[PDB]
Amino acid sequence: NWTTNLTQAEQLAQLIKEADALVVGIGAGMSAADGFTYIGPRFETAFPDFIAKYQFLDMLQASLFDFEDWQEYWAFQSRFVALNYLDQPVGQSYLDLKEILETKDYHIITTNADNAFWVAGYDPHNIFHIQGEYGLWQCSQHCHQQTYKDDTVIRQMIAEQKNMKVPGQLIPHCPECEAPFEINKRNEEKGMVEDADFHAQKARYEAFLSEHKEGKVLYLEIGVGHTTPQFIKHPFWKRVSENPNALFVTLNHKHYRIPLSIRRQSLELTEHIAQLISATKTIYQK
Ligand SMILES: Nc1ncnc2c1ncn2[C@@H]1O[C@H](COP(=O)(O)OP(=O)(O)OC[C@H]2O[C@@H](O)[C@H](O)[C@@H]2O)[C@@H](O)[C@H]1O
Ligand SMILES: [Zn+2]
């Protein structure tokens, strides 16, 4: 029953059913599993200019690169936003997970910044985008705590750029301090602009955690790696340690070693996320 000869999907379906509540942590693996990849042909097709000039290995690296000027920054990012936010289609695993979660008390924290939850029709009140969203902008000097958006300008930038540069007059500027806008993204050194909406999401997430300090709480970690373990992986480990009745279930095709404190409360499921979620949904629905 509630315990870490069944298939991975059978084991997952049963735990979800049995859980009092689910705390679901989603990282880049879930998007990669639906084909929203950041290395290979998807990246090569979309950015052959930038790859030819900078020898970028992957789209994450390129999205973090300190470009020479804001004209180049916005040429790259406008296209990046269109690929992963304006025009990214619905992923089947986001739809399959949503159906499973419909019958459960749950909350989601995600380090992903793509459109995946929105095109899959999730209630925004149930999701905490701790790393911001590609569709949003912030003052590059973080001069005040407000995010902005303007998809029309993004499309202008895609249309008007040439030679990896947006025309200067199209670069958007913070109305308070006139610094250029940048993507709402968390820097290690400078942090992230966290506006009223961000704090509302955080408070909802913290509320849910406060309500589920006890009981059969399933901490379900999907496609979370080592890139930024401080947001999901490590906090989950700690929650599971602090509640002896919690379980830690990680959906990941690579092995990340689990702390000694929670070895007996942990389960690693290595099946390809898309396949696993699909098979789990099928079982869970019978
Ligand atoms: N099909 C799959 N099935 C199962 N696991 C998978 C699959 N595809 C990828 N994974 C796993 O998903 C994980 C992705 O890890 P990272 O690339 O570290 O992604 P993430 O944990 O989300 O960290 C990314 C960090 O950088 C920022 O872009 C982002 O905002 C976040 O803070 C890896 O452990 C990988 O093994
Ligand atoms: Zn400003």
Image (cartoon, rainbow, N blue to C red):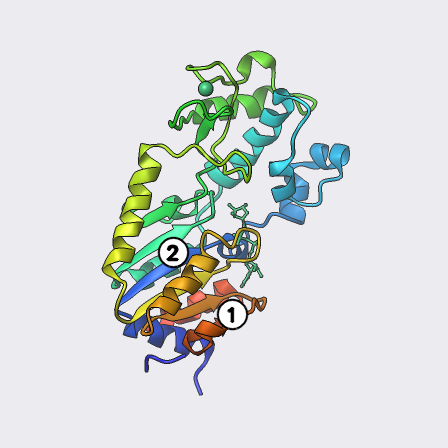
Residue at coordinates 71% horizontally, 40% vertically from top-left? Answer: 56
Measure the alpha-carbon separation of dots 1 and 2.
Answer: 29 Å
Label 1: how many residues lie within 10 Å, few (<14), some (14-19) or many (20+)?
some
Q: Is residue 60 above or below residue 285?
A: above
Q: Secondary structure at mark 1?
A: loop
Residue 104 in view (yes/no): yes
Along the line of sight, the residue nearer the viewer: 2 or 59:
2
Name the residue carrying label 1.
258
Q: Is residue 218 left or right of residue 142?
A: left
Can you give x and y, in whole percent of width and height, for residue 164 in the image?
67, 25
Residue 95, disc: 2
Residue kind at label 2, given as amino acid type: Leu
Q: Quadrant of ligand 2?
A: top left
Quarter of the image holding residue 248? bottom left
Can you give x and y, in whole percent of width and height, for residue 279 in the image?
43, 71
Residue kind at label 1, given as amino acid type: Ile
Q: Secondary structure at mark 2?
A: helix
Can you give x and y, in whole percent of width and height, for residue 6 in the image?
43, 84
Label 2: how many residues lie within 10 Å, few (<14), some (14-19) or many (20+)?
many
